[PDB]
Each structure stands twice: as structure tokens, then as C-alpha cells.
Length: 80
Length: 94
Image 1 (tube, rainbow over the protein chains, first blue to last red):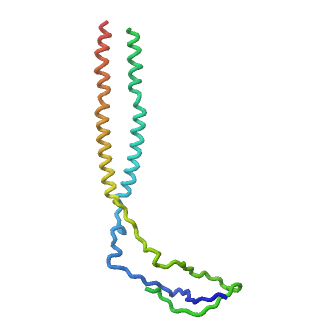
Image 2 (cartoon, chains in turn brown, yellow; image 1 turned 180 degrees about the vertical axis):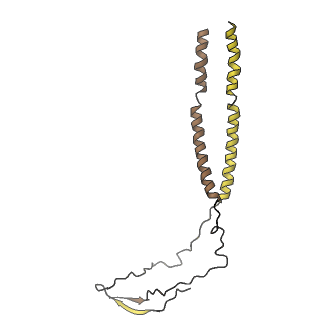
Image 3 (cartoon, chains in turn brown, green; image 1 turned 30 degrees about the vertical axis):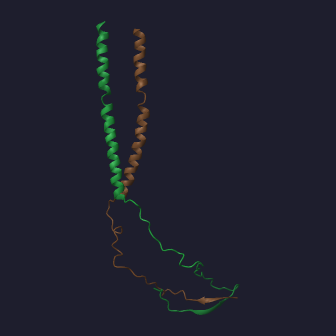
């Protein structure tokens, strides 16, 4: 024995919300083809790429003290 | 505010085994609607425009540093040609 009140599930059932005068013209509903978010994402990706590339250049160019000593010292020994 | 409905309410006494045309009742929770707080979109502290401005300022700083690296590292061939040529001439003097 289970009892409760019932209300008919009718297709005619509609809901009536209310909208304020300042609803639709929120600034974000209407947006241009180009906003700041896409530039932010692309610029951050480029910044990370440059951060990696500077480190790669640092490790690629760290041989100058070795690239010069092995060119100068043997000539020193040869002359000496 | 109440959604419209032609039928107010009626008296129904359901059974267990013989629920024919088995419907789907709209279940309701038991905690009061006073505990169910209204939704708020927490706006971020910064806006994408301010993000563009700050990131562009940081790019300008990084580019200035890279330009400094360029001017300090572009003279290395000049150092090469300034240091070895007198020594090469001295070796030729022999």
C-alpha cells in the first residue's frame, strides 16, 4: 500500500519565468570575431616555446671555453 | 511563478506488482531548498585583455633581454678577427 498525491504530466504544462530589462544585452552574448582569449593562448604557447628555445640555445652554445682552449693550448705547446 | 497545469491534483493509490505503463516519477530530494544555494559565476580576478597586456609587457622585457644578448654576442666574430690577425701576421713575420 503506497499512496501519494498525483499531478498530470501534461504537454500543456508550461513554465513562466520572468526576465529583467537588462538581460539579453550582456556584453559576452555579442562578441567579435577576434577577442583577447585566442591571443592569450597563442602568446602563452609562444612564450613557452621561446623559454624552451633559449635553454636549448644555452646548452648548444656552452662550448665556447672548450671550443677556444682546444684551439689555443695545442698551438702554445707546439711553439713552446 | 508556478508552471501552469490544467490538473490540480487527484487521489492515487498505487500498488507494487501491477504498475502498468511504468512511468518515471520526478524524484525530489529531502534537504530543504534553503540549503541549496543559488548559483554564482565566480568572475576571474583578471580579464583576457589584462592578460594580453601583461603577457605583451613580459614579451617586451624578454625581447629587450634577447636584443641585449644579440648585441653582446654579435661582436664575437669581431673579437675573433681582432685577436688572431695580429698573431697571424706575427707568425708570418718568421
